[PDB]
Image (cartoon, rainbow, N blue to C red; front, side, top):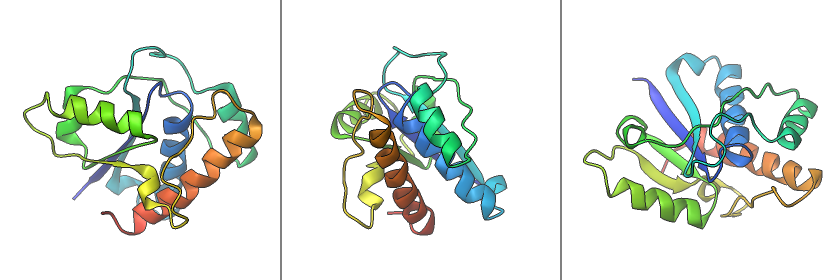
Length: 154
């Protein structure tokens, strides 16, 4: 049974592509990437076609993680095909819940990625108006949450 997770933010250039690349590293290094469909997407259309924020890329390169992604907006189909849709903050969640109610088939469990944090940091804050340290915090949160989600899904 092939499992799937979709990481979601507003733009799909900062937080979600990081979480996605973090997770694809986890499963790849445990020999199970073949068992996982992994992706990320945006609630809005602002960044469509764009690569990840360069600051996020630089952060990912310091941790030696390849991050290669073209921003895309979430579709009605994503709700039917993904087992899990994990977002970053409360407005993401509100948006996703909104879209999920326009759809016939919602297989996806929609949750904050942070609800998996062992350290109870619910929200993964947007680093967009911040600095490198803010990107680093996001990365560390993703590692914690992804590692926990991979072990045991709600």
